[PDB]
Image: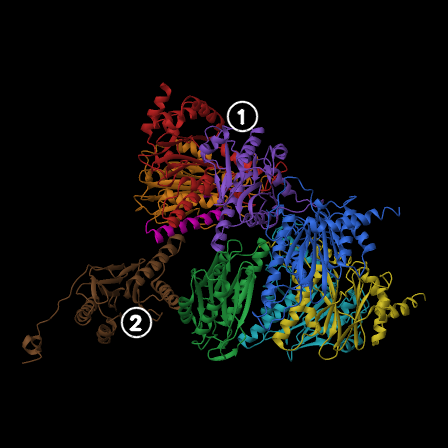
């Protein structure tokens, strides 16, 4: 049996780890995801795959917990994945448990960067121990914590991760980066970020208009807190606002996609 | 809780004799009076236990097997009596260390090349070798008598003298040990190996004048 | 005792063992499913190698629990592994929540087993796809699970050999209005399209989700539907 | 690289499983099983070329439980091992459920066992086709129906009306298909069945068989236990074949 | 690469590592055995490499229980592994089932054990055939388990390098009539004829039986009968 | 007794398309009162509320285990747990610990949001359910609460009528229990509306 | 290089990974050891990769116990492991028998860790010399990656070893003083080192027979040796 | 468990997996450590400063305990694991021995984890070198390096990552003992600029003094880059 071991956790001659390089290739094949970190929230816009007219919805009762590209990890943490979808679900479940174990132990939300380290430790493991292949997945995590506010990390199959103001994973990430470079700034509203996210996404998948059918958008923003049950624990402090991960219905997203056609029409006038 | 009563043994010039009643009791109940409590082990040894027969049976099987296999599987000489006894004693001890004690006292005899061996081992792994040995009430009733016969014949006993004194003790055990019967077997270890006698009884005396109804009456 | 992985990435980023397992899983016979407003139907060819096989004993459609069913394509015995696990999961869930497992949760559980065999050491992936059809609080469902562990809700689909053509023919005839009598009729018509030889209540199996339960049609019940096509 | 381990080829096939099927025919022995209205028979060749070998000592028929026989065809020691596993399975099952394992369940569990060897690397698939025969109680009336379940090295389990495995399993099958267009095989008698089985064996192996070159196993509704059929009675069937 | 591990079938459903272990047995010293109505006799030609061995060295015949023995043919160390397993089975039969292991059972157990090492990439097949000779309640019995784990009962049997000739000589014997006394003579005689002298200059012939005269105990035969 | 150490009582009762669940407010170590502001209710979701009684550390631990389970449920399943599942779940959890139990005694109220079917369930500490139609209860004042609820409770009360008899019952019974009191918190749960109320009680 | 597993014999009866581990010890800095009746001497080329290194930190000589020293050549990090085990073993011996461990017993227990590979992926690429003084007086042993200890009277390990076994053959007698030993040590290092022998470039220690204690020469005291030559 | 032997000797004495880990460390960003009288200075290259990375300060020099700081070169994610282990070790140690971990003790622990991973079946080596710097609880400053073989060594100054040996050759020439805080920072900046391009947004620099660890603000750093780039013309 050892003659047939492909030696996934070995170094190659340039200190490269081939299985991790090739997981990355697998990710650059995946549906693009854009993330834009404002100060009023974070936006994830992702390319869905082409919607065959025989696809059904799963008819889930909670519309905001998951979509095709976007998943909620906790009240305050969302992500989007590119790469081997099934690997994603393995990790996503791990990230969910981790965030809730943190909450078990401390009774407060896990910070985004710790959730992220946990996730990427789980990936790093598979690049060092165990003789199996790595997870072929890249997250964009988003969320909000009291330490750093809105955050947006991205992970790689190596287990490295990085914080960004905006970023892209998946198909034409190099191209999308270059375009966010130019148009991101530090003082964006949520609406501005939603625009930027769509202009870039529509520019990477080469469409005149944004194709509502092929796009999912999620937003992580703070909203008024409703269920302050204060007679039930009198000493507990409940913040006025709380984070919410939201996946946009086709209708909530229609305006924002029109408004990004209009800033793609008004950029082909100057030319 | 089938249990076996006394065992007694004595060295004579030439061999060893061991004797036991053929009885297993269950508490006070005399349950089986035809049990061959002495058991040969290998070609030169025999063993008999006082106490839990089930423990005895499992232990004696373990030892018999060890002996037989050591010899069948390797081109080696059968284990001597001391070696078997050693094994049995360490076995019994290991069980007391596991809190799974072999709840018997055992007497062990054996002869090889006119060297004789007589030892006792007890539930906790006590072991001792002597010219006579007993367990159960044997140890309280017969040892003193057997000891007395070896003080008086310091040159060793003959087989007949030894068998005379063994028999005297069986009779006494019969009278004073409750859980007993007047049916005994005696193993005899000598040069030739070990023979177990057919079961036999001893003559009892019950007609002392002081045992009469008039004398033993509580009220005149 | 082999603990290294068999499925690995290749320089283009592909997991080739999984493409091959996917190839294996489209070499089965045709199975297909049709969701309708009031139920789901799944249906498979049982192409028995010979007439001397007791066709009663071939099962291509399976109950996983009262409310959910599956069929499959590709390698039978691999699928038998999945079905056994899925049955257990349905029951574990009832034991815990004393309700029936929602199809979405069931398929995610299956998906997960498939994924483990794409990464865990020593094992190859499963060479079969499933359709899973069932009914929960969110209504009727029909899912396809592939060996990648990926899964899709569908309104209608087909896995196995004649499947591209069967899918094409379901695209035409499918309507979101469809009731279940028409769904069955469509399912059976779709099979019949690419069926070498007469369809019988022997060489076909059919499952329906109706009301709150999944049932494999009897040969009696299936013969009444096959007299109308 | 795929030919030697249990991974998929590009065509989506498992070489080691296909090759395990060749292990089934390599010995050159054929087996046939057949059910009639109230019995099931399995006939396998029993070839003792070595004059000095002790015929009663080598067999491809095995009681799995009192009510389930099986015939292994293929690599003999692999068959013997599956039988052990079957036996264990059957006995663990009786302990757990208090009842004798139904033969379709036993087959299924042995198919699960095989399947595993095709998905976990470095375990050689057993190169046999297992053929369990037995009776099976129906829940309606409580009547016993005869059953033949095979399991093959891929783990594919199936129930059959008649079935052959081994060398010339194709020409045996072809013969039984052909004789299934005439008669209805589940309305036959243990005699007419055995005749068909034996005739199929004879057709396939291109020779007339003698009694001592086969070994025949049987379960019947009357006597459900699986029993080696005595030679006297196999001789009489073989006589009944050469005639009619 | 089809032939490096016993976990692998060739394209014709052969397992080469087993055929190869087989060749180890065929290139080995010859054994024969005969199963009479009064018992089993097994004999085997020990080929020494040195003139200075002790008589007794490299016994290829082992008792496995009172009533059963195994003569090994092929790699002696591998056989002593089988002999150990046979002995554990025999002990188990006595310890758990309080009966001597029937010979067919013992040989099946031996076969299962040998076969197991033909299934898994991590072990190799054994390079020895065991001849099992029993005389328990199933009567006189002679089996052979080969490296594949295939087990067969025989009236007479020959293994090793002179096997083809020794079988021709064993065919001349009348198994229905032959007695353990005669067989010790014949079987030993056979191993002297088929022994090749200019190759293997040093050799004794070890013989053992289990029979009615030996009180159905498996024992080397006294070196007066040879 | 370990179940009485921390004090506290809880009670839930059904009406027409509503329930009330109510706890007292005390937290003790036996007769030492530590706090008078410790209601024992937890809200799982709009339609389920539960209370725990028993050793306070286990109330805390177990409630936290329940909140992990329920939040996990809601992510995996993308819906709210329902009271039947919820109670099954709890029962399961308590029974896992059958041989070394959580000293708690949950009391669960729930209302199907559609139907308005109301489900109450109380359990012993190893998770034997009690699913009556009227009212369930647990804790130090449980004998007296059965007294009162038997007497006062009737079928098909409305939120308000039902609140009044829940409160009178909790208070009357807590006034006879040394280990329960300092008034009560009550949640009235309908399809449309949740109403929490802090009720004035004795300071002994 | 994964063609042959690690437990494999060559056709000459050598285990390959052992022969290779030995090859790695010829790339190491030279170390050496000299038994005298007055004591043992160990000396090592430090072979620092820069003047910026703090030379105490690249310690090729290590107290195992008050009376035992070791000096490695080869893979230093591997040597830290062995010496940790020796230290633990030497101390367990004091603990258990209330006396200092013999030098041989110590070397054994350091080889007892080197047998272990299949556990350890590979052998240690390290040879030690272990000088000490016990009841049998001064002693010098060598461990190899084989796990085979060998008492010696003088020895070298490292790139030097061949040139340094020339010099021992000529100048070493069983009866030299501790100062003539120090001297022969440092001579040999002068001759085989790459760099110019200076008092920081080398490491010298002795275990004296008289007190049975180990002294590590400071740079000062090593100059005091270079002085007389 | 998977326990194949990954790190094995090849024929000429080499452990390829360790040579290749070391190759992964030559591809990593430079880092530099300098030891002065009362200061240790750790300075590292940043990857650049794309307008997209979070303008919130992310440190590339990691704190291991109050007193100890660690830069690395090589695989980020391997490093992160080592560091977490180091962090957790320093706490284990406090917790067992009340005292705080000497730097050298921490370094040896880390180097042992590195070594251990060149000899554990199932695992490849960490592809990480580290520079570690700090003060014991006695005011003495230390600076160490580990490489992937598990070898550590104390230095007066050191470099790791790309062109380590160019930088170390440079530093051998200049470096004097008993520098001041400000001469250390200068010397480190100078040394890094031997291989890094600008000194603008691609140098983080940490200054460790007994009981006080302080990163240069991007402003304080730039007075030093001009003061230095103006000294490189000559």
Q: Is residue H196 visible?
A: yes
Image hue for chain G: cyan
Which chain gets the yellow colouring?
Answer: H
Q: Quarter of the image holding residue C157?
A: top right
Identify which residue, G51 or C174, lies in the foreground: C174
Query: Whole-percent x and y of residue C155?
Result: 60, 40
Which chain gets the brown colouring?
Answer: B
Which chain gets the purple colouring?
Answer: C
Left or right relative to G207: residue E115: left
Query: Whole-percent x and y of residue B158?
Result: 22, 68
- Give above or below for G21 relative to B93: above
Query: Tag 1's secondary structure?
Result: loop
Left or right relative to E215: residue A116: right
- Give above or below for D144 relative to H71: above
Image hue for chain A: blue
Which chain gets the orange colouring?
Answer: E
Image hue for chain D: red
Query: Tag 2's secondary structure?
Result: loop
Left or right relative to D34: residue G229: right
Residue E93 among magenta residues: yes
Q: Is residue F96 visible?
A: no
Q: How many marks?
A: 2
Query: Whole-percent x and y of residue F70?
Result: 55, 59
Q: Mark 1 touching mark 2, by CB under 8 A? A: no
- Give above or below for H67 relative to D143: below
Residue on which disc 1 sits: C197
| Residue at the farthest top position | D243
Which chain gets the green colouring?
Answer: F
Name the subunit of mark 1: C
Residue on which disc 2 sits: B130
State the extent of the magenta-drawn residues as a range: E72-99
């Amino acid at each position: 049996s050892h003659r047939y071991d492909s030696r996934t956790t070995t170094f190659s001659p340039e200190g490269r780890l081939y299985q991790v390089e090739y997981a990355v290739e697998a990710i650059q094949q995946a549906g693009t995801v854009i993330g834009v970190c404002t100060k009023d929230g974070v936006v994830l816009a992702g390319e869905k795959m082409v919607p065959h007219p025989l696809f059904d919805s799963e008819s889930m009762q909670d519309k905001n917990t998951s979509g095709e590209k976007m998943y909620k990890i906790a009240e305050h943490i969302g992500c989007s994945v590119a790469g081997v979808t099934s690997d994603a679900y393995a990790l996503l479940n791990y990230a969910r448990l981790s965030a809730l174990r943190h909450q078990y132990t401390f009774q407060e939300p896990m910070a985004i960067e710790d959730l992220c380290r946990i996730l990427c430790d789980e990936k790093q493991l598979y690049t060092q121990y165990g003789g199996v292949r790595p997870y072929g997945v890249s997250f964009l995590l988003v969320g909000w914590d009291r330490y750093y506010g809105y955050q947006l990390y991205s992970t790689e199959p190596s287990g490295d991760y990085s914080a960004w103001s905006a970023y892209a994973i998946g198909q034409n990430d190099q191209v999308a980066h270059a375009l966010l470079k130019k148009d991101w700034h530090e003082s964006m509203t949520l609406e501005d970020g939603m625009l930027l996210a769509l202009r870039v996404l529509g520019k990477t998948m080469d469409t005149a208009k944004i194709d509502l059918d092929r796009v999912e958008v999620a937003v992580m923003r703070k909203v008024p807190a409703s269920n302050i049950d204060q007679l039930l624990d009198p000493f507990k402090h409940h913040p006025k606002t709380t984070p919410r991960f939201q996946i946009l219905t086709r209708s909530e997203l229609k305006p924002h996609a029109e408004r990004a056609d209009q800033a793609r029409e008004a950029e082909e006038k100057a030319e | 809780m089938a249990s076996g009563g006394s065992v007694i043994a004595i060295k004579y010039k030439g061999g060893v004799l061991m004797a036991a009643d053929t009885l297993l009791s269950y508490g006070s109940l005399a349950k089986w009076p035809n049990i061959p409590r002495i058991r040969l082990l290998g070609s030169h040894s025999a063993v008999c236990a006082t106490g839990s027969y089930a423990d005895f049976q499992m232990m004696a099987k373990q030892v018999e097997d060890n002996i037989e296999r050591q010899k069948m599987y390797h081109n080696v000489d059968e284990l001597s009596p001391s070696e078997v006894f050693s094994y049995l004693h360490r076995s019994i001890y290991q069980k007391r260390c596991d809190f799974d004690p072999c709840l018997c006292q055992m007497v062990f005899i054996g002869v090889r090349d006119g060297e004789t061996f007589l030892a006792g081992v007890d539930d906790v792994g006590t072991r001792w070798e002597d010219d006579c040995i007993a367990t159960g009430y044997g140890a309280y009733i017969a040892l003193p008598l057997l000891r007395q016969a070896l003080e008086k014949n310091p040159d060793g006993l003959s087989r007949g003298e030894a068998m005379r004194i063994l028999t005297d003790c069986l009779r006494v055990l019969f009278y004073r040990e409750c859980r007993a019967i007047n049916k005994f077997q005696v193993a005899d270890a000598a040069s030739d190996g070990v023979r177990i006698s057919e079961p036999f009884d001893v003559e009892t005396h019950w007609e002392y004048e002081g045992y009469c109804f008039e004398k033993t009456a509580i009220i005149r | 005792e082999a603990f290294y992985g068999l499925t690995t990435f290749s320089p283009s980023g592909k997991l080739i063992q999984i493409e091959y397992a996917t190839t294996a899983a489209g070499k089965g016979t045709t199975a297909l499913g049709v969701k309708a407003t009031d139920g789901v139907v799944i249906a498979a060819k049982k192409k028995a190698p010979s007439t001397l096989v007791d066709a009663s004993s071939i099962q291509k459609v399976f109950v996983l629990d009262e409310h959910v069913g599956c069929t499959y394509s590709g390698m039978g015995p691999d699928c038998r592994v999945l079905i056994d696990s899925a049955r257990k999961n349905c029951q574990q869930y009832k034991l815990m929540y004393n309700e029936p497992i929602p199809i979405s949760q069931l398929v995610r559980k299956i998906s997960a087993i498939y994924q483990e065999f794409t990464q865990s050491g020593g094992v190859r992936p499963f060479g079969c796809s499933l359709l899973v059809a069932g009914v929960d609080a969110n209504g009727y469902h029909l899912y396809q699970v592939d060996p990648s562990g990926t899964f899709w809700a569908w309104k209608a689909t087909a896995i196995g050999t004649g499947s591209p053509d069967a899918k094409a023919f379901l695209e035409k005839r499918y309507t979101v209005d469809m009731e279940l009598e028409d769904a069955v009729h469509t399912a059976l018509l779709t099979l019949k399209e690419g069926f070498d030889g007469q369809m019988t209540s022997e060489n076909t199996q059919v499952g329906r989700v109706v009301e709150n339960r999944f049932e494999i049609l009897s040969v009696d019940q299936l013969r009444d539907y096959l007299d109308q096509i | 690289f795929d030919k030697y381990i249990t991974v998929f080829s590009p065509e989506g096939s498992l070489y080691q499983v296909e090759y395990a099927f060749k292990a089934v025919t390599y010995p050159g022995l054929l087996t046939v099983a057949i059910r009639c209205k109230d019995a099931v028979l399995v006939v396998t060749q029993h070839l003792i070329p070595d004059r000095l070998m002790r015929p009663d000592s080598v067999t491809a028929l095995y009681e799995v439980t009192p009510n389930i026989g099986c015939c292994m065809t293929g690599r003999a020691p692999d068959g013997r091992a599956l039988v052990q596993r079957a036996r264990e399975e059957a006995s663990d099952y009786q302990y757990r459920y208090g009842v004798e394992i139904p033969i379709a369940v036993l087959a299924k569990r042995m198919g699960d066992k095989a399947q595993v060897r095709t998905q976990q690397a470095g375990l050689r698939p057993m190169g046999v086709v297992s053929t369990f025969i037995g009776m099976d109680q129906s829940d309606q009336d409580g009547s016993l129906k005869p059953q033949i379940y095979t399991v093959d090295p891929a783990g594919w389990t199936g129930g059959h009306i008649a079935c052959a495995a081994g060398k010339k399993q194709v020409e045996a099958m072809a013969f039984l298909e052909k004789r299934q267009k005439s008669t209805e095989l589940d309305a036959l008698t243990q005699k007419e069945a055995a005749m068909i089985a034996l005739a199929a064996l004879q057709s396939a192996i291109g020779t007339a068989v003698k009694a001592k070159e086969v070994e025949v196993g049987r379960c019947t509704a009357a006597n459900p236990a699986f029993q080696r059929v005595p030679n006297s009675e196999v001789e009489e069937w073989l006589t009944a074949v050469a005639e009619a | 690469g089809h032939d490096q591990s016993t976990d692998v079938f060739s394209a014709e459903g052969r397992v080469f590592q087993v055929e190869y272990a087989g060749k180890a047995v065929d290139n080995s010293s010859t054994a024969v055995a005969a199963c009479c109505k009064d018992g089993v006799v097994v004999a085997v030609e020990k080929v020494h490499t040195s003139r200075m061995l002790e008589k007794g060295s490299n016994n290829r015949i082992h008792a496995v229980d009172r009533q059963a023995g195994i003569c090994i043919c092929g790699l002696l160390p591998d056989g002593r592994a089988i002999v150990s397993r046979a002995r554990q089975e025999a002990e188990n039969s006595r310890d758990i089932f309080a009966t001597p292991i029937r010979g067919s059972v013992l040989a099946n157990r031996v076969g299962e054990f040998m076969h197991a090492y033909t299934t898994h990439f991590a072990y190799r097949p054994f390079g020895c055939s065991a001849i099992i000779a029993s005389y328990a309640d199933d009567g006189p019995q002679l089996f052979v388990s080969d490296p594949s784990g295939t087990v067969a009962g025989y009236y007479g049997v020959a293994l090793g390098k002179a096997k083809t000739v020794a079988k021709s000589e064993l065919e001349k014997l009348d198994f229905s009539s032959l007695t353990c006394d005669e067989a010790v003579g014949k079987l030993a005689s056979i191993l002297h004829e088929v022994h090749d002298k200019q190759k293997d200059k040093l050799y004794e012939v070890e013989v053992a039986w289990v029979c009615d005269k030996s009180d159905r105990k498996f024992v080397h035969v006294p070196a007066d009968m040879v | 007794s370990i179940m009485a150490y921390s004090g506290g009582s809880v009670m839930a009762m059904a009406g027409k398309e509503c329930f009330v669940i109510i706890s007292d407010n005390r937290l003790g170590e036996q007769l030492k009162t530590i706090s008078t502001e410790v209601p024992k209710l937890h809200v799982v979701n709009d339609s389920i509320v539960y209370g725990l009684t028993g050793l306070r550390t286990d109330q805390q631990t177990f409630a936290n285990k329940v909140q992990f389970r329920t939040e996990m449920y809601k992510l995996r399943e993308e819906r709210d747990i329902t009271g039947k599942a919820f109670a099954a779940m709890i029962t399961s959890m308590l029974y896992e610990a059958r041989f070394g139990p959580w000293f708690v005694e949950p009391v669960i109220g729930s209302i199907d949001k559609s139907t308005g079917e109301v489900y109450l369930c109380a359990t012993d500490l190893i998770g034997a359910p009690c699913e009556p139609e009227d009212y369930v209860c647990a804790g130090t004042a449980a004998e007296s609460l059965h007294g009162m609820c038997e007497a006062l409770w009737r079928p098909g009360m409305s939120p308000e009528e039902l609140f009044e008899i829940a409160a009178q019952a909790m208070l009357s019974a807590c006034d006879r229990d040394s280990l329960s009191g300092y008034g009560a918190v009550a949640m009235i749960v309908t399809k449309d509306k949740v109403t929490t109320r802090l009720i004035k009680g004795r300071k002994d | 290089e994964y063609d042959r597993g690690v437990n494999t014999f060559s056709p000459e009866g050598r285990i390959f990974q052992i022969e290779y581990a030995v090859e790695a010890i010829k790339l190491g800095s030279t170390s050496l050891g000299i038994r005298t009746p007055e004591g043992v001497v160990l000396a090592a080329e430090k072979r620092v990769p820069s003047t910026l290194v703090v030379p105490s930190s690249m310690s090729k000589i290590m107290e195992v116990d008050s009376h035992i020293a070791a000096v490695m050549s080869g893979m230093v990090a591997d040597a830290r492991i062995l010496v940790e085990h020796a230290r633990v073993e030497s101390q367990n011996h004091r603990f258990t028998y209330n006396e200092p461990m013999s030098v041989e017993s110590c070397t054994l227990a350091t080889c007892d860790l080197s047998i272990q590979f299949g556990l350890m992926s590979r052998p240690f690429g390290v040879s030690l010399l272990i000088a000490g003084v016990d009841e049998k007086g001064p002693q010098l042993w060598q461990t190899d990656p084989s796990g085979t200890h060998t008492r010696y009277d003088a020895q070298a390990i490292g790139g030097g070893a061949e040139a340094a076994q020339s010099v021992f053959t000529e100048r070493y007698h069983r009866n030299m003083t501790l100062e003539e030993g120090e001297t022969l040590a440092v001579d040999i290092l002068k001759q085989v080192m790459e760099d110019q022998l200076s008092p920081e470039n080398i490491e010298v220690a002795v275990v004296r027979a008289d007190d049975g204690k180990l002294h590590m020469y400071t740079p000062t005291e090593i100059k005091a040796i270079m002085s007389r030559m | 468990s998977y326990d194949r032997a990954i790190t094995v000797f090849s024929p000429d004495g080499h452990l390829f997996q360790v040579e290749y880990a070391q190759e992964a460390v030559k591809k990593g960003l430079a880092a530099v450590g300098v030891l002065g009288s009362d200061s240790v200075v750790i300075a590292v290259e940043k990857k650049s400063a794309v307008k997209l990375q979070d303008s919130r300060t992310i440190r590339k020099i990691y704190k291991v305990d109050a007193n100890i700081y660690l830069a690395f070169a090589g695989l980020s994610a391997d490093a992160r694991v080592l560091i977490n282990k180091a962090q957790l070790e320093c706490q284990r140690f406090s917790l067992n021995y009340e005292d705080t971990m000497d730097v050298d003790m921490l370094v040896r622990y880390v180097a042992g984890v590195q070594q251990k991973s060149t000899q554990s079946g199932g695992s490849r080596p960490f592809g990480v070198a580290t520079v570690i710097g700090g003060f014991n609880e006695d005011g003495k400053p230390h600076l160490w390096k580990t490489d992937p073989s598990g070898m550590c060594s104390a230095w007066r100054a050191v470099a790791i990552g790309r062109h380590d040996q160019t930088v170390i050759e440079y530093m051998e020439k200049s470096y004097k003992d008993g520098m001041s805080r400000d001469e250390c920072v200068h010397f480190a900046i100078k040394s890094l600029l031997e291989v890094v391009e600008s000194g603008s947004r691609n140098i983080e620099l940490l200054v460790l003094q007994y009981k006080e660890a302080r990163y240069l603000t991007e402003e304080e750093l730039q007075k030093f880059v001009v003061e230095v780039e103006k000294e490189r013309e000559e």
